[PDB]
Amino acid sequence: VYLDRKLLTLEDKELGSFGTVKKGYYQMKKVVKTVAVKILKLKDELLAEANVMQQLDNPYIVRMIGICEAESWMLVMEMAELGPLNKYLQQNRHVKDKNIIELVHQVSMGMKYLEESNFVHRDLAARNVLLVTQHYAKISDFGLSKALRADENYYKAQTHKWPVKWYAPECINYYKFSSKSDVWSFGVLMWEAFSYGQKPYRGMKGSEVTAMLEKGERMGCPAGCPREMYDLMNLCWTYDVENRPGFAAVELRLRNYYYDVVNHH
Ligand SMILES: CNC(=O)c1nn(C)c2ccc(Nc3nccc(-n4cc(N[C@@H]5CCNC5)c(C)n4)n3)cc12
Image 1 (cartoon, rainbow, N blue to C red):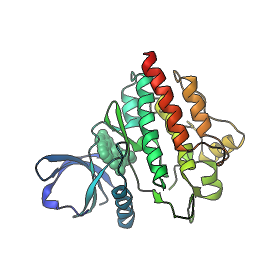
Image 2 (image 1 turned 90 degrees about the vertical axis):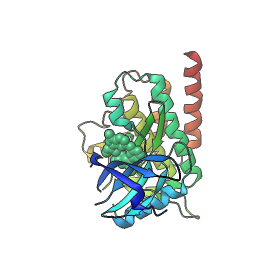
Image 3 (image 1 turned 180 degrees about the horizontal axis):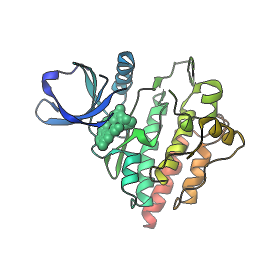
Image 4 (image 1 turned 60 degrees about the vertical axis):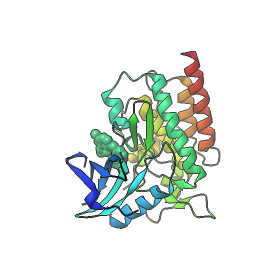
């Protein structure tokens, strides 16, 4: 878990600026590993974030190499070279619809695993999906993540920063976070991906988003997004937690549509 700082080389320039994200290199048993490092420069939160990641083992989740306590607290992770999914899509507007399905399906596989492992992500958004390649997505940013209690299906937040546009109505109304509330967030993530990284509920206040959802209104279908994918987004946005599908059902719908699109092309 605790890394040797002598074996870590950080780059001067930062990838993003909580703290900062920097590129580095970790001298391993034989090969040198390119890493992305979360630098605090909050400590308990970074250690809790590292503890969650240490427990996760899935191809569609960012792997943590370890933690290092130096001039600042550091979270060292395997590098996903292409960066955040939203920024990638904003910069590469010609990514094909089939490719977008492939990527959101990968996110759904990672989330199906998280749900099976009884962890709630609580910040599932396109800015928190990183690309290894144009055809390989991983989920990152476990800072708000919680291991569910053995006797409960949800995490109850004691007191209300929250990305409200990604949050299910029960998160807002009852401060209850479950895998079903991550399904809601995943619906918003699908909308962002098919909208090529555009922000959801454009120009609206958090209170206006709450009022809109309460009226039963939902975001429209993004340009070029297939009806089947929009139908899935709307299903993720099922107001009532009990009637909302879980990730096993969401991943299966995506898997089947993806292979239908693959074999049609
Ligand atoms: C803010 N800008 C960036 O992160 C970023 N910009 N560019 C150009 C990048 C290129 C590669 C990677 N590669 C990577 N590979 C593995 C892990 C990470 N991580 C990033 C976060 N936080 C960022 C804050 C919210 N979501 C992401 C965490 C926790 N891990 N990044 C990240 C970035």
